[PDB]
Image (cartoon, rainbow over all chains, first blue to last red; front, side, top):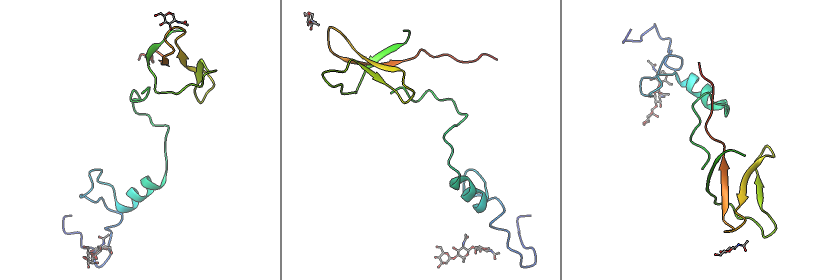
Length: 49
Length: 49
Ligand SMILES: *[C@@H]1O[C@H](CO)[C@@H](O[C@@H]2O[C@H](CO)[C@@H](O[C@@H]3O[C@H](CO)[C@@H](O)[C@H](O)[C@@H]3O)[C@H](O)[C@H]2NC(C)=O)[C@H](O)[C@H]1NC(C)=O
Ligand SMILES: *[C@@H]1O[C@H](CO)[C@@H](O)[C@H](O)[C@H]1NC(C)=O
């Protein structure tokens, strides 16, 4: 719900943060920033220069 | 070989004609007449689904 009042239980750290364009929670965003990945599945035509 | 030749930014020593990448294959040549260093980029290829 938009109210997000659960009787004193604060879930702001686990629920999506709408401020970020990825809509990930603060904890999920932290987890993604901690893991380093170079072998991306993205198109890679931006090297050779 | 087969590939696209481009102007290189590599500085070859007077005794070096070829360069190697991180996987020990050819990635640059010195033109035997102009002494310009050229980068070699393999021609684009990939899978077809
Ligand atoms: C649920 O918990 C989070 C995290 O504890 C609460 O957010 C936090 O709220 C406090 C007070 O509003 C923020 O501190 C203030 O930050 C501003 C930043 O400009 C600063 O000027 C103030 O002096 C003060 O330090 C804190 O930064 C903020 N943290 C996060 C991660 O949002 C949230 O309000 C809690 N919600 C409920 C319903 O209890
Ligand atoms: C070959 O002759 C041309 C004449 O313009 C000169 O520019 C070039 O450097 C020469 N190459 C060698 C390897 O002597």
